[PDB]
Amino acid sequence: ADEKRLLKCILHDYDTAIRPVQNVSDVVNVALEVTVVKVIDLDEKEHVLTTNGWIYHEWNDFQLKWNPSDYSGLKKIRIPVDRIWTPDIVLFNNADESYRYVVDKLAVVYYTGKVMWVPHARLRSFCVLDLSRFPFDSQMCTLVFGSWTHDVSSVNVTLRNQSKVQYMIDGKEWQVTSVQPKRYQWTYNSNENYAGIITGIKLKRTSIYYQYVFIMPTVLLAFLTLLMPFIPPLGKERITYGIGLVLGCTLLLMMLSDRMPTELGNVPVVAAYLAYVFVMVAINLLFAIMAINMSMQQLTRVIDRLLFGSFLVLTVVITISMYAHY
Amino acid sequence: ADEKRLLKCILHDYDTAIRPVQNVSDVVNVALEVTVVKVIDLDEKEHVLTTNGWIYHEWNDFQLKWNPSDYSGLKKIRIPVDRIWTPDIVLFNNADESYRYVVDKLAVVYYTGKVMWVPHARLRSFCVLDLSRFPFDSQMCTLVFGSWTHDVSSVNVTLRNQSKVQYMIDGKEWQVTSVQPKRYQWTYNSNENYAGIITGIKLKRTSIYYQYVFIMPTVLLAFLTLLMPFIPPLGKERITYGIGLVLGCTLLLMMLSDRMPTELGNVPVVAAYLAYVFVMVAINLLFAIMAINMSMQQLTRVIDRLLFGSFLVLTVVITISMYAHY
Amino acid sequence: ADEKRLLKCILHDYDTAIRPVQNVSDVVNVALEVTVVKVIDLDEKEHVLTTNGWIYHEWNDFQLKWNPSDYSGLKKIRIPVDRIWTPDIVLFNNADESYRYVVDKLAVVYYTGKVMWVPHARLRSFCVLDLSRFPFDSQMCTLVFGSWTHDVSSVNVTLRNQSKVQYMIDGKEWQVTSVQPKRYQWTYNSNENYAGIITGIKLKRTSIYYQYVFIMPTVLLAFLTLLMPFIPPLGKERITYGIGLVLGCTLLLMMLSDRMPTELGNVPVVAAYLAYVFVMVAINLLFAIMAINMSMQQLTRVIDRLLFGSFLVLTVVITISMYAHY
Amino acid sequence: ADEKRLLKCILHDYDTAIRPVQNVSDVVNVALEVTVVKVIDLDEKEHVLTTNGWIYHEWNDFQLKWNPSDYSGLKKIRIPVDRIWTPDIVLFNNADESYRYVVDKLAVVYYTGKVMWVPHARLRSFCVLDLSRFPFDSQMCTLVFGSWTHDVSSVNVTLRNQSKVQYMIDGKEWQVTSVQPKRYQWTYNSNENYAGIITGIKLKRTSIYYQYVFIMPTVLLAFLTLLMPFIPPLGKERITYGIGLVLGCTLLLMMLSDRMPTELGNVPVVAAYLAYVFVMVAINLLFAIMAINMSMQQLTRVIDRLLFGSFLVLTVVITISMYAHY
Amino acid sequence: ADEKRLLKCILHDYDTAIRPVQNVSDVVNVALEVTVVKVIDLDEKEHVLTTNGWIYHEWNDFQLKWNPSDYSGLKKIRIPVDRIWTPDIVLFNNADESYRYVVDKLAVVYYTGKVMWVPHARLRSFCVLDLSRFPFDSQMCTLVFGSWTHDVSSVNVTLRNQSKVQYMIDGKEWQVTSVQPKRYQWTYNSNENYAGIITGIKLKRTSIYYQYVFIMPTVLLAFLTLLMPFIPPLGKERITYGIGLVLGCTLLLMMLSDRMPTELGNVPVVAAYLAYVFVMVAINLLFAIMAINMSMQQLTRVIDRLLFGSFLVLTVVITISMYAHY
Ligand SMILES: *[C@@H]1O[C@H](CO)[C@@H](O)[C@H](O)[C@H]1NC(C)=O
Ligand SMILES: *[C@@H]1O[C@H](CO)[C@@H](O)[C@H](O)[C@H]1NC(C)=O
Ligand SMILES: *[C@@H]1O[C@H](CO)[C@@H](O)[C@H](O)[C@H]1NC(C)=O
Ligand SMILES: *[C@@H]1O[C@H](CO)[C@@H](O)[C@H](O)[C@H]1NC(C)=O
Ligand SMILES: *[C@@H]1O[C@H](CO)[C@@H](O)[C@H](O)[C@H]1NC(C)=O
């Protein structure tokens, strides 16, 4: 055969651990590129971002050299990674118990030693979610690619010469804004220095799920508490309303506690609003109890009207403070 | 033996990476067929469709050639895939961390080099679910099969010559409509072009689960709110009803939020209806509070009757807008 | 040694892929037996039945032959399956991503070529659950064993000669009735025919869990709705009862929706009973609202009594329709 | 080297399948000991007991013999199990898909052939939980260790000579009582007999979790129903109380159904008590409805007092029946 | 090549099991260091602490010796662990079924035999959580590193010479306080002694999640019960309030039972407070029932006022007992 003849004369003394270089002091310019093709999910229960992405590798090789003219062309050979040298580049923040590479069993090589291994991975990364703007947030996620084993004396992890990765993966759940990747030198200690590549994926929330399960029932309960103090205390239904509002706000807290995770850096604004409808039922229940105790002059109507006006201006300033997000 | 004699003279210099071809510029017509035998599940929490399917492969081989007449027949040999060449065809949208394969340890070969490897897989695919018609949807799922490693210069991923796959797997949960598969040339870049095969599985919802857990309690709460404004405000039970309707609609929202996932492209119509019963309770609670404040002329009966008529025509036009799905 | 001397002269040219036969047209009678020793679980969320079972294999061999008399007895040798031929028999309906096998690393061989490999597996099978009789069902489960790779021209998957597997594994959760296994010839196409073995495990429900979490609260709410219309409408508690019945039936629907899975072929009878207590609260709430509107002649007592009698006969005929299951 | 010289002359013809023995009719006394160091969890959803334990093995060897005096001592050599013979001892009731053995890559050998392989495993075992005493139960768990492959003609699975394993692992969740292990001969059939070792771990419940989430709210609802019939029926709050008791007992059933698993052999006593507070709320709601129908002579006070006394003596005899557990 | 020439003359007779030493009685000083870089999660459902950490290893070697001057420098060689000796150091409390290792496929070696293998792991450890201070706890976690296979006669697991690991990983969920690691000699038996290293990670709770889902609704329900007894019993709403308080406290118990795990050593103080609001509703419901029975002299106002004062002083002393934590 033709490919078998060249393959029998290119891995004669090739190990999967020898760094391909001519001079020991010389390094290898292992280029890298990250291309997220589809963001799978973002769960804040354990700060996990699952994406599907291509991890483009490109390093020069010294031993994979052949002349094409005596081998009848054959400028591209498909070589598995189990019989070729492989860099130890990994996610710095991995959530899986092990690092997995879908379709990582093949890698092309060129006639100039231009291995272009492109595996595809379900990357599970860790990002800091600023949930003070929840749900209408713009918290970017950073993915780190580097080698923990060898350092800048062995490899030089750089960005791709052509960095045309300024895409926008408009999904049905998030708006994805790609950031042009940067290179930073992470230092293990003072004497030794390493390399690393940061890529950024900004996520913009656009779904109307959280405006349906949280915002609309909370603003409707706020509207109900705003309409609460018009009922006279002698009707024997104001306290029943108030305790029904307590039960409804407790069910809203049950939904929020089952949905919003344990990771809090700042209190969410929907959680702050739920605290508000609560601190209202408590305040208007106190005023209703005091009104029905005073009823047993009819001064309570003016007190309820001024209380309604104060709650009106407080609720409208809280809702226009909330509306600055959207 | 007879099979051992032929097997000892067919893998003398066979590697698991050499592409079987005679001329380098020539390609191999790697045929493909997808046959879903049983759709396991469809979960919209992370856009996962789990199916059980056969992935029929058929490629011509150049090195697996023998004359049968001097080997006493033996037109079919069972050869494991670990000692034979294997294409790198995969799902383009895989949800598992690694590609699973059930019964992939054997593959038949013919005397003309007609390897017919048929593995079986639990394919976990990603589809775009148009949930605006939820639950009575007809959102098709697309499964993509292609090679990321080699391109049209090496293999040619084509359809089966006999494409008799127009079945209909009538299950107890979905109606499965198979679509005749098509071939599209996905391009990694401008200079290089690759191959891919799209197969389609249309899912028709036929279960009465979502008509029992969502539609019937929501239409019963709508019927209850329709019957609400007949109660006189002096009976001290209209506000109690209204707040009980608030609690019941909150429990319905709790069931919907625990069931309907975070992925929303459009608001579901059952979710829109749950918004309607909510906006009713709020509106009829406002009118009940204003009626019991006016009661403390008896004009409220005509107001409640016209309100009941307006709610009657609005509820019936909303239900006949809903009934166009079913 | 004695075993090492025979082992060094029995795997001289043995591969893990050569089918052991003398003539090519001859087949091998690969016998099979299934013995479920303990049914682990049955979850209807994805039609999964987890059992622990022995998969008895017995095939004649042509190459594993030795005379015992010159080897000092030694009629039984323990040989691992990694160095011996192995059939590709599998579950036709597997739920795991890969086929698991517990204690599959050893297999006895006899002096006549009588390999008796008995692995043990946690089989995850798929069955059609007729949930119209839920919870008091008798839906059998079918487990299929066959080879997808080779056909009746190579192996002949037959029953055990001694089929004494008519046991009864009486567990604390189910009653297990073993069915005598049958053999059917599944056909991949018209020209080629394959083999398969069906074994049956009938499951009888005997637990009092579903009679405690579903049947007793639903029949108690039905009893409460039966006792509902005796309250006079002027007591201002009939509508409160009715809405409390709505809340209780909604909590019952919440428990049922969180427990009963998405797979419905037919509506469960407990679900039908729940849709009935709901259709009652709705009907008696309508009659209570009309009675309190008519009260604002005292004809409502006779109407409530005839309504109570009609609901009495309807509830008793529904409960004696339900009682035919148990 | 010294260890390399002995290691190069001890595995010259050693396979991982030859049973180490001199005479074929002779057997090997493979001793065994189980030492649970920490019980991880016990979940009754699928009868799983997760423990961390040492599985001490000790078998005599015939081929691992050397004289120490010409090898400069070296009485202990660390040998991995991949290059030494290994018994096929396993859990008879395993919940994992495949057998795990954390720290199983090394095993010491002595100069007399005294291999002392001690792996450590997260054993997932199956026990029969007698939940009639739930939560204050004393249901022991049995762990079975035996070989399915070879029988008493090959190995003899016996106890340790020194059985000092009478410890007591006092944890924060359970009290662990070790049982001295026994040996039983499990029979695959009539002609052939095998060996097995039973070890027992008795679990005593001591946590106050289930006395907080179940016992205290149920006894408080029973106290509330005991205090229920003192309210006069003309106050229009007795029926509201009763339906609030129905809602509270329904929430208690929701907590119990979400916590107590589907496996029931007998009804739990806490489940029987929730059942009492229910049938109790039903009976006093019937008597309250009949009292408010009779009110529309004032004989109902004596009826309510005798009903309260009967409920008092019934509740106190039920609570002293419950108190015999604790 | 240069690296290939040295690599072909350094693993000539190297096995992955020979302990590298010159004299048999001599030991190897296998140093160790633990560096937690990011604490992933702490779940008390099964006492699991998931951290991401570096496990620094450093042992002297006897066989990995070369002179650099005739090899043109090359003081550092990257060698995979599959072809080099590896200590069996592990977590003593592991929650995973098998020991996972991220980037463990490479390890540097120096010219003096100074292997510096640094793998990175998602360590799942077990700690005793003193939940009597929940949520404002300071329960440290202990991670144990040692070898179960060989003992102090073979290796000597010691600290790093430079122990500069006094960092503080200030996260958004916990405050991490590193403890300087210590060495303890765990004994398998009396005759033999082993080695082990304890490292400590103290976790300080700083999130406001549990102050939002538990503390604020419980203190608001306590405030509501404090405001409860002012309502006159003739208003027919005191019993309705009390039963609404019962329903709200039951929903709070539902949230607590779904969140707080089964592992209890001591009752949490938030759980004790939830007991207090419950025992109040029960006590004030008893007093409300007795007041409405006495109403059917007006001495109940003074009784309610003294009851309110006693509940005021009891609630304020309970809240200032709670406030000592924060
Ligand atoms: C790695 O590449 C960067 C790119 O500018 C260069 O500045 C740096 O000197 C390189 N490192 C080495 C060791 O050559
Ligand atoms: C692959 O097959 C299609 C089928 O028509 C053909 O048009 C195309 O030219 C083929 N590609 C190559 C490279 O031969
Ligand atoms: C397989 O066994 C059945 C048992 O009766 C027999 O009828 C059939 O002919 C056999 N098949 C072959 C190919 O021998
Ligand atoms: C195995 O050991 C027991 C211990 O008493 C002994 O009774 C039995 O005979 C032994 N079995 C064989 C086959 O030697
Ligand atoms: C291990 O190191 C400690 C450090 O002080 C030392 O005391 C001890 O003797 C050493 N053990 C051996 C066996 O050398």
Image (cartoon, coloured by chain):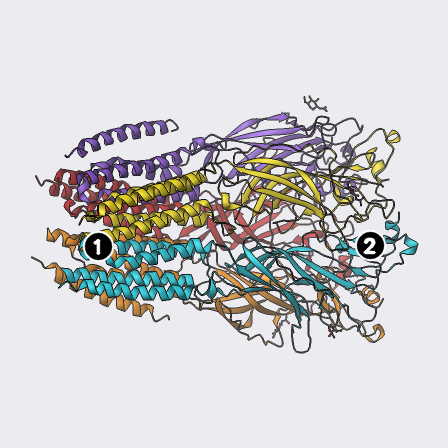
Chain colours: A cyan, B yellow, C purple, D red, E orange
Please report the residue visible at 40 percent of the width from the left and 65 percent of the height from the top. Answer: A320
- Amino acid type at circle 1 is Asn
Give the image quarter of residue B58: top right
Left or right side of E149 for D170? left
Disc sitting over residue B293 in the figure:
1
Q: In this view, does A47 lie above or below C199?
A: below
SS of the residue at dot 2?
loop
Indicate if the residue with disc 1 has its beta carbon within 8 Å of ligand 1: no
Could you say whether the residue bearing mark 1 is in a helix, strand or loop? helix
- Residue D225, visible in the rendered structure: no
Residue B204 locus on image (x, y percent): 54, 37
From the viewer's perspective, is residue C143 above or below residue A122?
above
Residue type marked 2: Lys
Subunit bearing disc 1: B
Front-most of residues E46 and B75: B75
**Frontmost residue, D301 versus E155:** D301
**Residue A58 drawn at (x, y percent):** 75, 62
Answer with left or right where residue E145 lies relative to residue A118: left
- x and y percentages locating residue C136 in the rendered image: 42, 32
Q: How far apart are marks 2 and 1 (CA)?
A: 86 Å
Q: Mark 1: few, some, or many residues within 10 Å (few <14, many ≥20)?
A: few
Residue at mark 2: A76
- Quarter containing ligand 4? top right
Residue at coordinates 22% horizontally, 29% vertically from top-left?
C306
Residue B33 is situated, as x and y percent measured from the top left of the image, at: 70, 38
Q: Quadrant of the N terminus of chain B?
A: top right
Pinpoint the chain carrying mark 2.
A
Mark in front: 2 vs 1: 1
